[PDB]
Length: 164
Image (cartoon, rainbow, N blue to C red; front, side, top):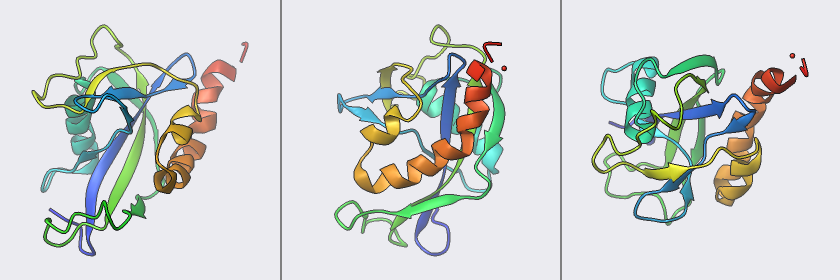
Protein backbone atom coordinates (compact mmCIF):
# COMPACT_ATOMS: atom_id res chain seq x y z
CA UNK A 1 0.00 0.00 0.00
CA UNK A 2 1.39 3.31 -1.23
CA UNK A 3 -0.68 6.52 -1.47
CA UNK A 4 -0.80 7.59 -5.16
CA UNK A 5 2.38 9.55 -5.69
CA UNK A 6 4.88 7.27 -3.89
CA UNK A 7 4.13 8.11 -0.25
CA UNK A 8 3.70 5.48 2.42
CA UNK A 9 0.65 6.30 4.62
CA UNK A 10 1.58 6.18 8.36
CA UNK A 11 0.55 7.38 11.80
CA UNK A 12 3.14 8.69 14.29
CA UNK A 13 2.26 8.42 18.01
CA UNK A 14 3.44 11.46 20.01
CA UNK A 15 3.15 9.98 23.50
CA UNK A 16 3.33 12.86 25.94
CA UNK A 17 4.11 11.84 29.39
CA UNK A 18 2.10 14.33 31.58
CA UNK A 19 5.27 15.66 33.24
CA UNK A 20 5.63 17.77 30.02
CA UNK A 21 7.93 15.41 28.16
CA UNK A 22 7.73 13.32 24.97
CA UNK A 23 8.10 9.87 23.52
CA UNK A 24 11.63 8.64 22.91
CA UNK A 25 12.69 4.98 22.85
CA UNK A 26 15.83 3.04 21.98
CA UNK A 27 15.39 1.06 18.81
CA UNK A 28 15.49 -2.71 19.12
CA UNK A 29 18.44 -4.41 17.34
CA UNK A 30 19.91 -0.99 16.46
CA UNK A 31 20.85 0.31 19.92
CA UNK A 32 20.22 3.93 18.92
CA UNK A 33 17.07 6.02 19.14
CA UNK A 34 14.29 6.28 16.62
CA UNK A 35 11.16 8.26 15.94
CA UNK A 36 7.69 6.63 16.07
CA UNK A 37 5.69 5.86 12.89
CA UNK A 38 3.60 2.86 11.89
CA UNK A 39 2.12 2.06 8.48
CA UNK A 40 -1.62 2.26 7.82
CA UNK A 41 -3.29 -1.06 7.11
CA UNK A 42 -5.38 -1.19 3.86
CA UNK A 43 -8.86 0.24 4.50
CA UNK A 44 -8.14 0.93 8.20
CA UNK A 45 -8.89 4.59 8.96
CA UNK A 46 -6.36 6.93 10.62
CA UNK A 47 -7.58 6.55 14.20
CA UNK A 48 -7.91 2.75 13.90
CA UNK A 49 -4.39 2.52 12.39
CA UNK A 50 -3.09 4.87 15.13
CA UNK A 51 -4.15 2.29 17.76
CA UNK A 52 -2.49 -0.38 15.54
CA UNK A 53 0.82 1.55 15.67
CA UNK A 54 0.27 2.25 19.41
CA UNK A 55 0.26 -1.55 19.87
CA UNK A 56 3.10 -2.28 17.36
CA UNK A 57 5.47 0.39 18.72
CA UNK A 58 4.61 0.93 22.38
CA UNK A 59 2.67 -2.25 23.18
CA UNK A 60 -0.34 -0.18 24.35
CA UNK A 61 -4.00 -0.75 23.38
CA UNK A 62 -7.19 1.34 22.59
CA UNK A 63 -7.55 2.37 26.23
CA UNK A 64 -4.07 3.12 27.58
CA UNK A 65 -3.94 6.63 26.14
CA UNK A 66 -6.07 9.76 25.45
CA UNK A 67 -6.00 11.75 22.19
CA UNK A 68 -5.57 15.50 22.91
CA UNK A 69 -4.73 16.77 19.39
CA UNK A 70 -3.59 15.65 15.90
CA UNK A 71 -1.77 17.36 13.00
CA UNK A 72 -4.20 19.57 11.09
CA UNK A 73 -3.39 17.73 7.85
CA UNK A 74 -1.00 14.93 6.78
CA UNK A 75 2.60 16.04 7.13
CA UNK A 76 5.00 14.53 4.60
CA UNK A 77 8.52 14.69 3.54
CA UNK A 78 10.80 13.17 1.07
CA UNK A 79 13.33 10.43 1.80
CA UNK A 80 16.94 11.10 0.78
CA UNK A 81 17.97 9.16 -2.29
CA UNK A 82 19.94 6.48 -0.49
CA UNK A 83 16.99 5.78 1.86
CA UNK A 84 14.34 5.68 -0.92
CA UNK A 85 13.38 2.05 -1.26
CA UNK A 86 13.36 1.18 -4.95
CA UNK A 87 11.85 -2.25 -3.90
CA UNK A 88 8.38 -0.99 -3.10
CA UNK A 89 6.12 -0.57 -6.15
CA UNK A 90 5.36 2.27 -6.55
CA UNK A 91 8.77 3.38 -5.32
CA UNK A 92 8.30 4.87 -1.90
CA UNK A 93 9.87 8.35 -1.94
CA UNK A 94 8.41 9.62 1.36
CA UNK A 95 6.32 9.11 4.51
CA UNK A 96 2.78 10.54 4.48
CA UNK A 97 2.10 10.88 8.25
CA UNK A 98 -0.60 12.22 10.53
CA UNK A 99 0.74 12.54 14.05
CA UNK A 100 -1.58 12.15 17.04
CA UNK A 101 -0.79 13.74 20.39
CA UNK A 102 -1.54 11.05 22.96
CA UNK A 103 -1.57 11.81 26.65
CA UNK A 104 -0.36 8.76 28.55
CA UNK A 105 -3.16 7.21 30.67
CA UNK A 106 -1.34 3.99 31.62
CA UNK A 107 2.45 4.17 31.60
CA UNK A 108 5.85 2.56 31.70
CA UNK A 109 4.39 -0.30 33.83
CA UNK A 110 1.82 -1.21 31.10
CA UNK A 111 4.01 -0.19 28.11
CA UNK A 112 5.31 -3.48 26.71
CA UNK A 113 7.00 -2.59 23.33
CA UNK A 114 7.55 -6.40 22.57
CA UNK A 115 3.94 -7.22 21.74
CA UNK A 116 4.73 -7.49 18.01
CA UNK A 117 7.50 -10.14 18.38
CA UNK A 118 9.72 -7.99 16.05
CA UNK A 119 8.88 -4.50 17.33
CA UNK A 120 10.91 -1.33 16.87
CA UNK A 121 11.49 -0.34 20.50
CA UNK A 122 13.41 -1.91 23.39
CA UNK A 123 12.93 0.67 26.10
CA UNK A 124 12.75 4.43 26.53
CA UNK A 125 12.93 7.65 28.46
CA UNK A 126 10.70 10.57 28.59
CA UNK A 127 12.86 13.48 27.47
CA UNK A 128 12.47 17.25 27.25
CA UNK A 129 10.01 18.46 24.57
CA UNK A 130 12.26 19.64 21.58
CA UNK A 131 15.02 16.97 22.45
CA UNK A 132 13.90 14.31 19.84
CA UNK A 133 13.83 17.10 17.19
CA UNK A 134 17.59 17.45 17.74
CA UNK A 135 18.20 13.73 17.89
CA UNK A 136 16.60 12.88 14.64
CA UNK A 137 18.41 13.04 11.28
CA UNK A 138 18.67 16.46 9.66
CA UNK A 139 16.09 15.91 6.87
CA UNK A 140 13.44 14.82 9.43
CA UNK A 141 14.34 17.40 12.01
CA UNK A 142 12.60 20.26 10.15
CA UNK A 143 9.36 18.28 9.73
CA UNK A 144 9.42 16.90 13.29
CA UNK A 145 9.72 20.49 14.47
CA UNK A 146 6.34 21.19 12.86
CA UNK A 147 4.82 18.24 14.70
CA UNK A 148 6.25 19.58 17.98
CA UNK A 149 5.13 23.16 17.28
CA UNK A 150 1.56 21.96 16.51
CA UNK A 151 1.36 20.33 19.99
CA UNK A 152 3.77 22.35 22.19
CA UNK A 153 1.18 24.53 23.92
CA UNK A 154 -1.16 21.49 24.29
CA UNK A 155 1.46 19.67 26.43
CA UNK A 156 2.86 22.80 28.10
CA UNK A 157 -0.61 23.86 29.31
CA UNK A 158 -0.49 20.80 31.57
CA UNK A 159 2.83 21.99 33.16
CA UNK A 160 1.59 25.73 32.64
CA UNK A 161 -2.47 25.71 34.24
CA UNK A 162 -1.30 26.11 38.84
CA UNK A 163 1.81 26.24 38.47
CA UNK A 164 0.01 26.39 35.47
